[PDB]
Every structure is written in structure tokens, then in C-alpha cells.
Image (cartoon, rainbow, N blue to C red):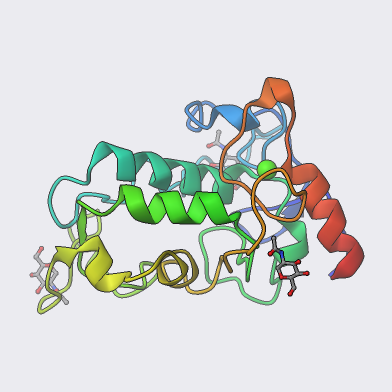
Length: 204
Ligand SMILES: *[C@@H]1O[C@H](CO)[C@@H](O)[C@H](O)[C@H]1NC(C)=O
Ligand SMILES: *[C@@H]1O[C@H](CO)[C@@H](O)[C@H](O)[C@H]1NC(C)=O
Ligand SMILES: *[C@@H]1O[C@H](CO)[C@@H](O)[C@H](O)[C@H]1NC(C)=O
Ligand SMILES: [Ca+2]
């Protein structure tokens, strides 16, 4: 555990520095200029490990567009943020890229994600493991009943903390405090997570 600021973990589980965003992640607009989902300077083998065109958000029927928007933000933060270094667990190489633990997600990001997913459906509370991937995309395992989102995630805390097995630990702090990570931002007005990484690098 060395470099914590402006750093990435790639799909081969080596640390790397960020760079200009790649074409696959074009919709991840906040990270266009400085991203861990970056172009490569060498002829590294091309294999997309992104969830953007891989994960089946509609495993229990149509996910409401408002819910999907949060999942896009979530995916973009995980795949592109160069400000998660303080939470990277380097011994764990079992995720598609970095394993992060207890990232202090801003209160608003979590509560509104939970609200906006009220009318969507899912079949499990931990989305990292346990899917049936034989069709190429993930489907619910046999016996895993589709239910309203709040059946499996009864509070915002349960959603944000459990969905990716403690990747997030929702904060009591809110946006603008410099003490929590937000899932999206306007880049022309500045990346607020840079300050947040600095704060926790000094504490962790
Ligand atoms: C660049 O290399 C990385 C690391 O292997 C890989 O994940 C990515 O798919 C490559 N980029 C392209 C252009 O596919
Ligand atoms: C996975 O899905 C396929 C059908 O696409 C099915 O044959 C198989 O039994 C499923 N396995 C589980 C564990 O649900
Ligand atoms: C959250 O809890 C921490 C630790 O107890 C405390 O320092 C801080 O004042 C709290 N922040 C808010 C916004 O409640
Ligand atoms: Ca960021």
C-alpha cells in the first residue's frame, strides 16, 4: 500500500496512473480528462471488462430509467475514478478491477439511489456474486425470486453498503463537505472527489 492519490488498479490488478478516457466509457462524462478507464499507450490486448455493456440491469424486468441512471453513475465511478486509492484493498484480485472497501459515499447519492429504484425489481441483495452467467449476461439463479428493490434493500444503508459487498460505506456526511465521495459531478466546476481522497489519505 503505497500511492493513494491519483491512482488506478487495472484489470490485470497492477496499479496504473490515469489518463484520457477511453471510447467505451464515453458516457462517463465527468472523467473525460482524467480517468482510470483510459486509453493505452502500448498495444495491450483489448478486452473490455466494463459492466456498461455487460451487466444485465434488467434481470428482473425493465429497470426504471431513474434507477438505471444511478447504476450507470455507480459503474462509471468504479471503473473511472482516480480518487478511490485510499480504499483500494490490494490483496484482493477477485474483482474485475480494483477491490474497494468502505468508500464513504455521500448521503444524498445513497438516499436518492435508493428512492429512485423503488419501482424496479431484483432477485438478490449481493450483486457481486451468485449470478447465472451461462447466457453471456447475468440472469437470476434458479429459486431466486424477483421482488421489488426495497424487498432486498429495505433502507438506503442496506442498498449502498450491501449491493457490492461493502465496497461503499454510506457516510453521514453530504455533498460539499469534502468528506464523502460522490458518484457524479460537473467537471467544468471541478472534481470534488480529489479533495476527499486527500482528506482520507491523510487519515488512513
Ligand atoms: C488497454 O489495456 C487494458 C489493460 O489490459 C485493458 O483492460 C483495455 O481493454 C485495453 N484498452 C482497449 C483499447 O481495449
Ligand atoms: C443457468 O441458466 C441456464 C439457462 O440459461 C440453465 O440451463 C441453468 O440450469 C442455470 N443454472 C442456474 C444455477 O440457475
Ligand atoms: C458524522 O459522524 C462523525 C463521527 O461521529 C462526526 O465527526 C460528524 O460530525 C458527523 N457528520 C455529520 C454531518 O453528521
Ligand atoms: Ca472521482
